[PDB]
Image 1 (spheres, rainbow over the protein chains, first blue to last red):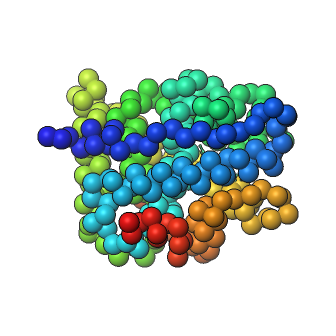
Image 2 (cartoon, rainbow over the protein chains, first blue to last red):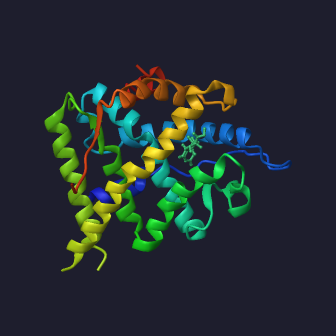
Length: 245
Length: 11
Ligand SMILES: C[C@@H]1C[C@H]2[C@@H]3CCC4=CC(=O)C=C[C@]4(C)[C@@]3(F)[C@@H](O)C[C@]2(C)[C@@]1(O)C(=O)CO
């Protein structure tokens, strides 16, 4: 009174709109520019979400920053996978209600490859038939899934918070009709593979960010984050926390 | 230090 799961549901940000002008044909540069700005704003929401997440603010401030910077992409990508799941059964990418990318719009030269790995995320929800509560739980667990090799400042606080939401995930499964053990295996397996698929998105992203000759614009929020997170990733100094080996 | 991030995290 109140249950953790109903706190998750209530703190979940409303879906943001892109304001994309589709009067004239899509240019890949300007689609990516529009996405980045949508992205900035969604990250800003993610930051407010995380602050309201029970346990998060017990962490040292620097650790709050680190976690958000390390996982923003997997959060954004997972939530995208969710909107594409419920909205079009994973057939189209639902970035915003006024920016859906179907098979055609994807054929943009630069787009196709990145788009497939994003599509791979929604198909997983389709295949595993993920519920809302399962998703909400898996989403916080992504926020806590990518850490400095050197560990955090608040390691023991962290370790506990992770435990709590691991158990909250257990509850969302059980809540949803013995073999619940198997579900947990698959869900935690899905969380594991995010590292790989989000890998690629982060690759393109650093690429488009680093190579200013591309004309892909980033908002301040993302730029600050990317330019701080890039050296850390390249130096191979960050670590994924996995459930399986 | 990402200034906007930090600004958000400290109220
Ligand atoms: C392939 C990458 C990964 C993309 C991101 C994937 C996750 C995401 C989901 C959204 O609902 C809105 C924006 C973001 C957060 C994103 F779509 C944009 O920011 C553009 C992005 C970084 C990318 O298109 C670029 O690097 C182009 O600059």
